[PDB]
Image 1 (tube, chains in turn red, blue):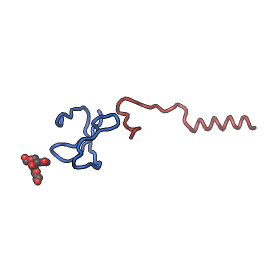
Image 2 (cartoon, rainbow over the protein chains, first blue to last red; image 1 turned 180 degrees about the horizontal axis):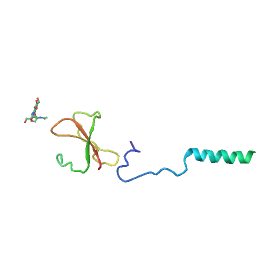
Image 3 (tube, rainbow over the protein chains, first blue to last red; image 1 turned 90 degrees about the vertical axis):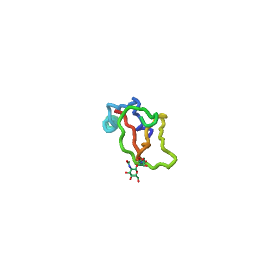
Image 4 (cartoon, each protein chain N blue to C red; image 1 turned 120 degrees about the horizontal axis):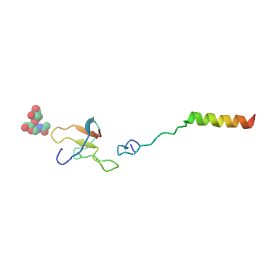
Length: 35
Length: 49
Ligand SMILES: *[C@@H]1O[C@H](CO)[C@@H](O[C@@H]2O[C@H](CO)[C@@H](O)[C@H](O)[C@H]2NC(C)=O)[C@H](O)[C@H]1NC(C)=O
């Protein structure tokens, strides 16, 4: 409940780049450096 | 205001297990989050507005 006790004005905002897009960039760099 | 338990917010219904001698409820931030009504014997939870 340590994550849900944020009633006292302490917010965490998500990153703009999600995990899927980061993994897709990683796959793109891997493909570009292998082929 | 239940015997000096002043606060601001809504009082939702909570059904957590307590003890007969335990009526107060605090949290990590040392704030009154769960309370027991003095007259009637159910449990309320303070949620901000
Ligand atoms: C507070 O006092 C009142 C009388 O002034 C009592 O409440 C009654 O409790 C009985 C329980 O057997 C109920 O059947 C009645 O309907 C209640 N009357 C009311 C609420 O007017 C009792 O002594 C105390 N009540 C509580 C909830 O502690």
